């Protein structure tokens, strides 16, 4: 299963909302998760099964989608949100990461 | 309380092999999958494979079949990944991780450098 993420990078100001998308090469039955990878930290699971927020994760993170098309959003951007985000499909007992999206903050 | 303790850095010559390990602590090692992921310099995360210690089942990224071999030792709660016939492109940071609806824990990551 192939995953294509978009955009590859973006720059946004604090307080705003950003949205990233991911497209699979086949129906992955909403079995998609989103990870945040901050430099110096290990990857962190934020959302799974398309829209389910991982316990302990801020509600500023959300997801939506179905079939082959999915979206992930970060509302009220904070400085600590600067990182690379990845979608991850986990259907058919396999894992496939999207190419990643580097999010940079502006001030 | 939960942690995945990853093994140290490695240096190997072309054609050689190395075996990385990850010891789990804080959760039932035999009822969850453990993943192995690669990240080459300046590149994104890549899935290598997964193993379910409870029964030994393994799943591999087609790209890594023939390169990576996953095993597990339930008595020591340790999962291992062997990289065979090492080459330049294998130089990267490798992570072990238990990541699912019930918990998200990653090893600190370890480097494998392949050079003559
Ligand atoms: C590839 O490993 C084996 O398949 C399992 C992968 C697991 O990925 C998790 C990723 C992220 C969030 C939440 O849980 C996912 C989990 O459901 C998934 O389970 C796979 C095995 C199975 O479907 O039972």
Image: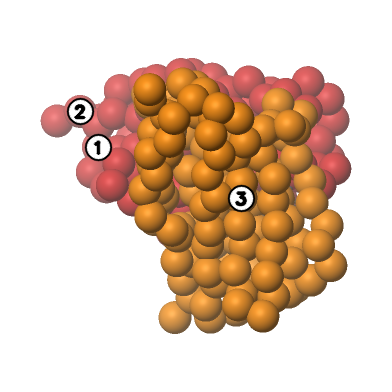
Which residue is painted at 61% across and 50% down in the image?
A: B81
Which residue bears the numbered disc 1? A14
Q: Is residue B32 above or below residue A21?
A: below
Q: Earlier in the sequence, mark 2 or mark 1?
A: 1
Give the Cα separation between the discs numbered 2 and 3. 41 Å
Which residue bears the numbered disc 3? B81
Answer whether residue B13 is visible to the viewer in this image: yes
Label tally: 3
Across and down, in percent, residue A84 comes to: 40, 34
User: Which chain is tinted orange?
Assistant: B
Question: Would the CB of label 3 be found within 8 Å of ligand 1?
Answer: no
Which residue is painted at 14% across and 30% down in the image?
A: A107
Chain A painted colour: red
**SS category of the residue bearing label 1:** loop
Q: Quadrant of residue A18?
A: top left
Which chain's residue wears label 2? Answer: A
Across and down, in percent, residue B93 comes to: 42, 39
Give the Cα separation between the discs numbered 2 and 1. 7 Å
Which residue bears the numbered disc 2? A106
């Amino acid at each position: 299963i192939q995953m294509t993420q978009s955009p590859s990078s973006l720059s946004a100001s604090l307080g705003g909302k950003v949205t990233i998308t991911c497209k699979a090469n086949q129906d992955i039955k909403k079995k998609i998760a989103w990870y945040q990878h901050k430099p110096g930290k290990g990857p962190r699971l934020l959302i799974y099964y398309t829209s389910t927020l991982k316990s302990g994760i801020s509600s500023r993170f959300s997801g939506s989608g179905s079939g082959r098309d999915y979206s992930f959003s970060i509302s009220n951007l904070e400085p600590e949100d600067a990182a690379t985000y990845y979608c991850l499909q986990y259907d058919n007992f396999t894992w496939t990461f999207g190419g990643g999206t580097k999010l940079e903050i502006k001030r | 309380q939960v942690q995945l303790l990853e093994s140290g850095a490695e240096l190997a010559r072309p054609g050689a092999s190395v075996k990385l390990s990850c010891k789990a602590s804080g959760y039932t090692f035999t009822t969850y999958w453990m993943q192995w992921v690669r990240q080459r310099p300046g590149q994104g995360l890549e899935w290598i494979g997964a193993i379910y210690p409870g029964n030994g089942d393994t799943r591999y990224s087609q790209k890594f079949k023939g390169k990576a071999t996953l095993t597990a030792d339930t008595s020591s709660s340790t999962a291992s990944m062997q990289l065979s016939s090492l080459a330049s492109e294998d130089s990267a940071v490798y992570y072990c991780a238990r990541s699912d609806y019930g918990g998200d824990y990653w090893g600190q990551g370890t480097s494998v450098t392949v050079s003559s």
